[PDB]
Image (cartoon, rainbow over all chains, first blue to last red; front, side):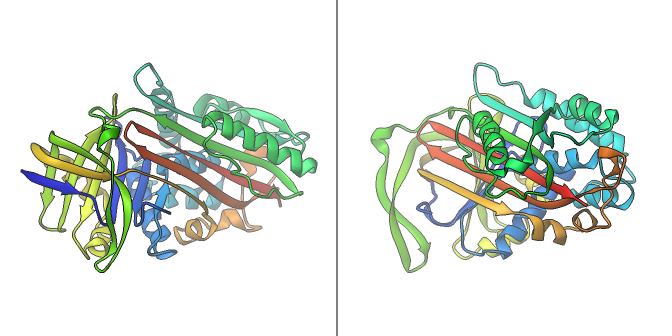
Amino acid sequence: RTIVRFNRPFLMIIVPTDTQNIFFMSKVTNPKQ
Amino acid sequence: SANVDFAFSLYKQLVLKAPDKNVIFSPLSISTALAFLSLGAHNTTLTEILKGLKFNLTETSEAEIHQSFQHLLRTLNQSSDELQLSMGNAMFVKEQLSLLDRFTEDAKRLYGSEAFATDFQDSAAAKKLINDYVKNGTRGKITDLIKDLDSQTMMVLVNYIFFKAKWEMPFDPQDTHQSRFYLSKKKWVMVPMMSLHHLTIPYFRDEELSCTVVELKYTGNASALFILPDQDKMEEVEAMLLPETLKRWRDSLEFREIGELYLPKFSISRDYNLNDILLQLGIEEAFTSKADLSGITGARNLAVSQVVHKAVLDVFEEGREASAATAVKITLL
């Protein structure tokens, strides 16, 4: 089965379903600040 | 739209300004606050602002623009029993500075604002009030937006967004574990990694830009798009963050059963002073003496001091929350 392992820098965008705008944009380089 | 366009424009700058740091901000909160600003802007001041927000001033009329955000604020503010989400606009105007009826009207009508009488002479207390209105609206997540407050201050426009929604397939606390997170190929650290098994979620392995896109929904009309760029493919990926890429990604996601998924539990909070970035996007006149904000008082006696922005994101087993707020400190000219 395919595995998704977010264990290196990644991006994350919080998007609504209808009105395409972007609520929160983020990139995680290190989980501990 | 222009919005997701403006959004990616700002992101890339925030990156150049600090390459390897975590980034977190709310585009919509910034667009609505600057757009709000437009109501007073005239002539060139206004032109610059609209274009900076990636709006096409020939296809979309000024009036078209404000009518939109109105409708958005309306719908956005639909915090019903399922997920929390609200946005608000306000302006603390110096106690004795009259503003044209039109401005005070369109602000309440189109952006839902208020005009609170503020004695900026008491910067200690003025800052207090404003900080408490944001803390209030964000349910106490954004503390101390206004770090400093000028004495010659005439008014401050502020916006804020609160969002709270649980996942739709929660992570079970029993499954969180200390594991390696690679800061780089030969550099790693231990962090709490959340899990999920035999999961059916939208998926897309983007071979072109070399990254895997995945989607996890919150209860209600909202979701989180995660993009895990390949090892050493982040630079490439960030370069292609174009409004066209996002639509292609969204349009390519198809349902797939994933054996096991791993996501780091984390919380990040960053704040900025957007002056420089906004000036690179083309919003320049509003910062000088040449600034025309005659829509506020009739007289051209105001100018932008600085625009700051704070944001917070908490990613936990129960989804959790995110909030951000923005303020435009206007001074006399």
